[PDB]
Image (tube, helix red, strand yellow):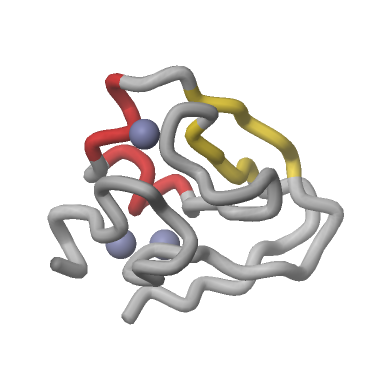
Length: 70
Ligand SMILES: [Zn+2]
Ligand SMILES: [Zn+2]
Ligand SMILES: [Zn+2]
């Protein structure tokens, strides 16, 4: 229920422990309210476009939702 579309220069966060593949990402809001802030995460700046995968159970091996969207 996030669905945020990233803007130019916006940080995106993946979790190296939980992402199903390297394109699985969270926006800043969802990352900071998720279990993955305590994991090995990777921040990549968006060039614009793409979207947050919070809530997609097929994107995450654990912790698919943040506290705001669960
Ligand atoms: Zn989000
Ligand atoms: Zn969320
Ligand atoms: Zn994780």
